[PDB]
Every structure is written in structure tokens, then in C-alpha cells.
Length: 284
Image (tube, rainbow, N blue to C red; front, side, top):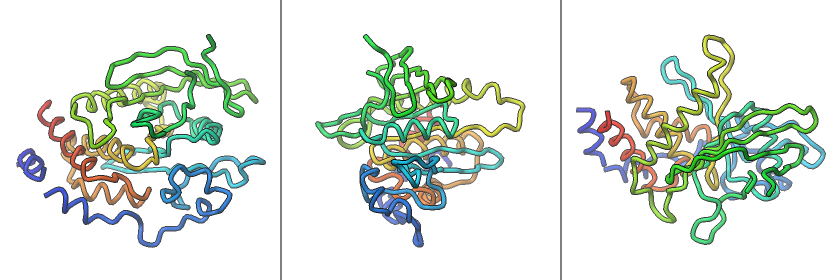
């Protein structure tokens, strides 16, 4: 029945179109400040005040503003923490790396190419003879890369220049999203999700059997809501399916939109989540 229910739905237009885009009484005071307008790629997509990612203020960035949201979801006993953010701008790369540093992030899931159809989606905030670049106070060095065609996994070393401390950050870039619509290769997106799962596990291995808080993974696309929402909703719903949790897809999307406005921007994106879930169940 469960499988037949998902396949049948794929009716989804009305289900999607009915879900509110944002919290009714949303507050976004810091994001709305004129000084923070230029820090948003798409002005209309901003974090709610209560769960924006707060950077330690600096002289140039006195509110410690970055267009990024803490997304926290508990499913049964399991707790998920993502930071959903925009593709960095040329003038926010240093903010991005400050965030990754301060939040203890080990994994970045970038669900976009830098440029698509001649349109900029994200700045190149990791190194392209020299394999390093310094963004503000953070030196980033590209160490290795595995290209799996649909996606590529790059190992980065990030050094906080003030303290000399270093961390490995894993950068997982999905490269198969077409200019319009959604990927035809659903299997490749599932494999990308598997790669994220793999990397999160190995980066958190030394926390196993402790009460240490698992750090968030960063998820971004262009504005940090469309494909970013697809990834997060897919991971959560796959978990729900694996553990037979009684959670409906549209209700989980509502929960996500209460934490970051506009998550999942198109019907094609929403339908794609269903395609991902159906293929996951078929694979199982």
C-alpha cells in the first residue's frame, strides 16, 4: 500500500501548490537591514531572525550576518541539523568560511554548478600551480578530488590563520542538475545522497559512543531553498521510509518552511522528491 500510495500520488501539483511559502508571522530584522541587502543573493529569500546563523561580529560585518538558517528536525530519537545557505557571493566567501569554521562543519553539500545556462549560481569559494586560496582569515587548500560524473567529492584543508588550527572539510558537489526542470538520472541523485551519508558517518566516527553534538552539514544551491530543499527533504523522507515513521511528505515540507522560507521552489522539484523516494523503495 505505502509504495502504491507514493506511485499513485505522482495529484502532487495541488498538494504542493497548497503549502504556504513561509511562516505567517515571520521576523527577519537583521536580514532586512539595508547593510545586509547586498549579502543576500536573492533579496527576497532570507533567514528568520530566531534561527539565522549568527557569525561572531567583525568590523565590516557588525551584525555577523550571513544568509543561512539552522534547520533542525527530530525524527523519533534521531536529530538532524543542517545549515541551509545561499551560494556564496564574491563578497561573502570569507563569511561562508567563518561560518563553516565557527559551526564545526566537516561537510558541504553543494547542489549546483557555479554557472548554469550562462547565469551565476555560486561563486567559486574553493581553490580552482597553486592549490590554495585565502578567504579573509581562512586558508583553504584543495588536496584531492574524486569525480563520479554525477557528482564530485573534494577534500579541502581549512586553516584558521589566527590560531594555526586546521580541519579537513569535505566538499560534495552535485553536477547533474539540468538548466531547467529536474534530473532525469534519479539513481545518480540517490548515489549523491549515499555519498553524503558516507562522508557524514566517517567525519563523525570519533563522536560515536559519546554525547558530543554532531555538527551540522552545510547545504547550498543558489538561493539556498530550491535544490537545497530537495536534498534535505529527500534525506529526511528516506530516513522516515527506512524506519517506517508516520510522516507525510507535505507535512515534512511545512516543517522545513517553518525554519527557512520557500524550501522547494517548483513542482518539478517537489515531484523529483517523490521520484527519489519511489526509486529508493524500488532499490530496496
